Length: 114
Length: 114
Ligand SMILES: Nc1ncnc2c1ncn2[C@@H]1O[C@H](CO)[C@@H](O)[C@H]1O
Ligand SMILES: Nc1ncnc2c1ncn2[C@@H]1O[C@H](CO)[C@@H](O)[C@H]1O
Image (cartoon, rainbow over all chains, first blue to last red; front, side):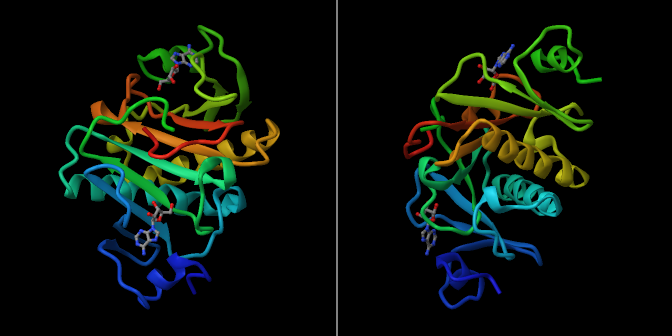
């Protein structure tokens, strides 16, 4: 359960993370290389390698990650907003093959988004 | 139906857009100010002003936007990957208050994501 990546280890608690939310579907934790004053990840407990591998039946789970991200952003005081990011594959900058939603805020986010 | 923003006008077809996908839940169309060789938006037909205003019952719809984004990215040949972005509020760089998912690819996306 949780798969064979860094994030599988986090889900199994084999290594800790700075956990800010947990429910039966997902986990949220602070990013170890933050790119903004607040930068956290929301990950499903189900191992989905990448967004391009998600199936139709995963829609509710994927949307759950954004609703959790909204809740966590509010808990962390992101009153002025935030940016949500999912990276796919090489061009997207994905390095860990377990779906993860980035939530960044606490500063003005620029454009383009990379 | 569709709300009182630019994107409401697009949903009602009062102004055209470069539509690449339509179903009963959402619309996808090319962005008018592209930041990558492929840059399109996926929007719900339901007016949700911003991700921070989405409700729990919207989870399936939000996840549908990413699954549509995955499908469109494949139709557009984004074999090397892509980045998905949702902007919230001022700090997120949101300018149109109707939820929209950006999908960018056809080049290496950089880090940080703005
Ligand atoms: N042990 C870890 N805890 C928290 N974030 C991590 C860990 N390993 C990698 N990351 C974050 O995972 C992301 C992968 O997209 C990165 O932003 C990276 O910094
Ligand atoms: N008529 C339009 N058709 C397509 N994209 C648009 C239109 N108006 C604004 N946008 C795009 O909407 C986004 C709002 O985040 C921008 O990336 C902007 O370029």
